Length: 429
Length: 18
Ligand SMILES: O=C(O)c1cc(C(=O)O)c(F)cn1
Ligand SMILES: [Mn+2]
Image (cartoon, rainbow over all chains, first blue to last red; front, top):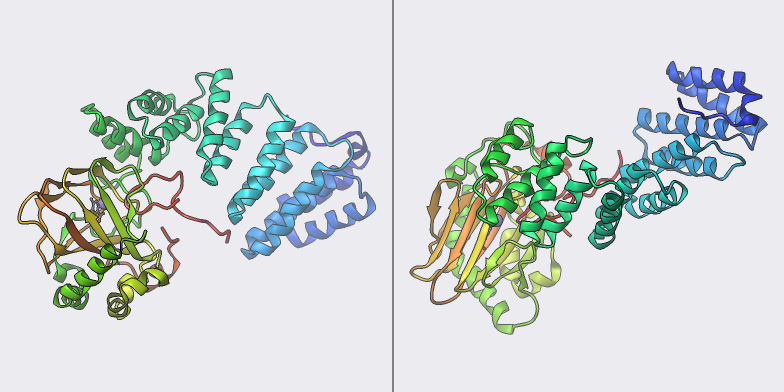
């Protein structure tokens, strides 16, 4: 069905088919030099140029080389600029370019290629759907939203556009509105709709509005492999890690860290309070849409295993203290931060992104009553100078119905069963 | 944007090829 040869390339179909046969049979070195010869003999051949690119692409996979792949990405573009490029070949070449650009993390370059693709094929629905993803991958939910509105103005039942539109709506806190789009799109079954994100957010959406069928969808997500359990709904996981909502210090093995936190708790408190008191902008409001109501702000010392040097100027002894514990300072899937919460605050039930961390909470200023945290089926409270430990990949929920402010210190650690290699290699979150 | 306490971003990791 693919029509990849223009009239010129048909005049040399035998040479092109010989080169491609070498590639399909795995003789990459041989194929590279065959298509190189063809590109040399026929500088204007689109098919010879595409074969060169596919061979560079294959050679990048064999060597696991980003640099080689960057070369393939440029050759795929050369294909699109040659004379009389068949439409099927033009689409294949630029689509692969954008896909490989995404693989490298060149999200801005992929977006440019995707904008050119949609401009070349205005009627290809799937290219617009992929353009929307391109916007989402750069954090441009406004342009992404327009793309999917366009799409389902033309094609109202495209399941892919439905779940992506509902995902965008929920991100904008259009909870009730996003439900039908997320719900219908999963039941569609279209390619790209069987994604844990959409199961995660549909259930959460339904939970926030009281729609008691949310857990029916979580169990479904569990059946599809997206959630380890109905309660533990993180999506960036290492399978087999001990899963329990509450931990003791002994169970984590990080007993010296827990001791250092509790023994030095007044020093940690006083530095955090001193930062509050200066009243600069260092405590930032929570900005993940997790609050039903109230006031919640956080002052972060470490994130993604990276020390915030300016923050540590405001809590210099606390930061010096923590350097002794790479299990937290090097936890590239966690943070170290102070968290202040004021009266009249309720945090929605929610889950963290990964099962590769545990969270330690050290009480610093805890009103005698009104402050609660539930994780899974158990509700606990903080105490000044004491550490609580839970797995925030389990659903958890917080209340602040006290008469004054509540301050804690949050120290993330690698899940103890993660190996040193896993701790060095896992992508940061 | 980053996924700190939740799963708000379309993707929570920044891939870098091989
Ligand atoms: O450590 C967490 O994951 C967490 C902490 C708080 C808090 O009370 O500061 C919260 F409301 C929700 N989640
Ligand atoms: Mn949380």
